[PDB]
Length: 36
Image (cartoon, rainbow, N blue to C red; front, side, top):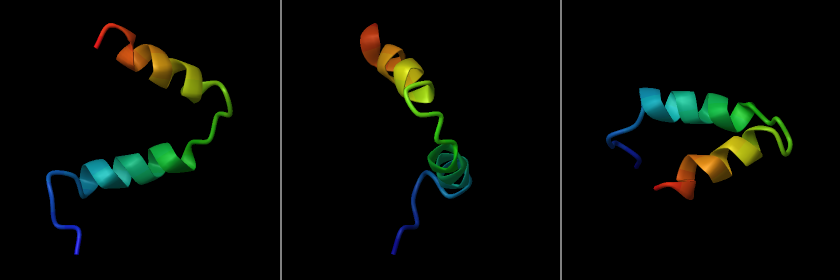
């Protein structure tokens, strides 16, 4: 089971998964690391 520090965040993540944005959100996600 997946009972963790997520759920609603995972719901957002699923929405983030639902958010395709091919090479759009992908690009931001790369730069989300970047200075990580």
